[PDB]
Length: 214
Length: 222
Length: 129
Image 1 (cartoon, each protein chain N blue to C red):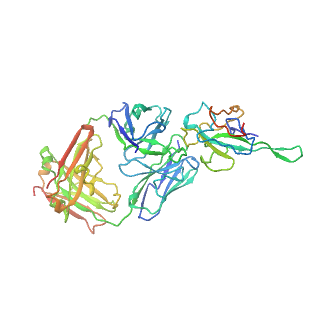
Image 2: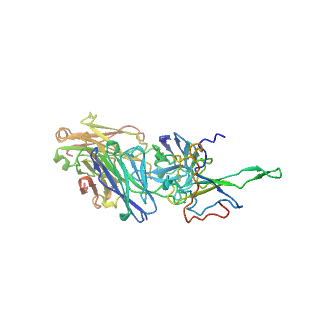
Image 3: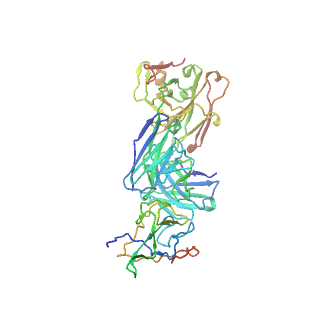
């Protein structure tokens, strides 16, 4: 099969910049058998370019495709925050039709510190015999962030899991949750539950805590 | 307008057969090519095959031994059968129309379904518990409070979460699920709202886990 | 000499008049039962020949138009519908714009030329045989 290799795997650019996405094939696909699709989170892909260089009619002319043989480019001018997406190239010059693995285009913005919130386990969950403590870091940039749990000043390791949203299409920020899981018995043995957050937008690490029962 | 919708089981045991159907509305199957495309979680797209409305097919050679695509014009549907599945077949499956409105016959996917996840696993379905993430003084930043719902211990993916039956969308963050060491998934969905509105506006998370028929509406209060 | 497998699969259409070959949209692809609906798309390419005339000066013979599946033959790299002199494009409903590598071209050492047949009801253009 023809293998399509996309470069770079990720791109991070400011609005108004011009983005250049590379797609290189393992064998020639001539000059009209390549398409580009845009995929936003949770959505189906959407046609941008076909025939290597022809633009879909609902797509603005700041998107353009070029190249021939094995070497193809998608150019996006005047990048916008809503251009956050994975861009895939796809060839139909050979069977089977194949896609590249995508280039994810992140939109750069000003540094924004997270807002930090902490949630004790609900009384409903505690009834069952387990305690989930949730720390939320909301609407920050860049994505890199460090979240540590302390329970009565004991640093936790190995008993929390993190999840991060995809970049927001409008404000280009990220949000993150960290969930600490403990048994009801362990939870009732300790008083102070703290989330410690390190992020570029904060001049130094910060902590948000609660005392169990207050 | 032309709309496509995938249907079929979300959970299939290894070595068994995956079956999906695409239902077309707002247009006819007839005169067009129709296609199935899949996307494993976190990965790229893979073309499975197409069918012309009158029955001719072409399949990806790596899947040919296992794939059947069929068309039923009488019901405006086409279908996918994939035999001998393994975990490598876990993916979101899309149906799509192939049609080039410029008249130059390009095989472009111009309309797509929303995609349906199929998980290949021996494990049984488990419905989630839904707990409130209540707003409080520790989830308040000045005029803004955060609240949410914790959707814990379900299998397989996915769950959907909306707020106020879809009326509340701004400021909502529904996190990607995490797989716990138990083999069950958990996720949270949060929203930020003005602090002044906490005693006067109602906030309800609408949780649906269709594999278990678990549907919950949970009002979240201080 | 040494043509290899670069020949058209079909016999040519000879142009006896002064107008280029052309077909109504949806018409003109030669019949080939060893192909599928998505295959039914390609170009005719004008081939000119010269001979010495009776007066001793070189002379053109009547042009001959040879069919090639899209993505094969002398213009294998040319996109469907490209405006190029001596090339005209044809496709049947159900065609896909993909190169027909799997059909390719013909080696006359191994296969004779298929007599070019068009479906009943094709508008055959003036002066073509």
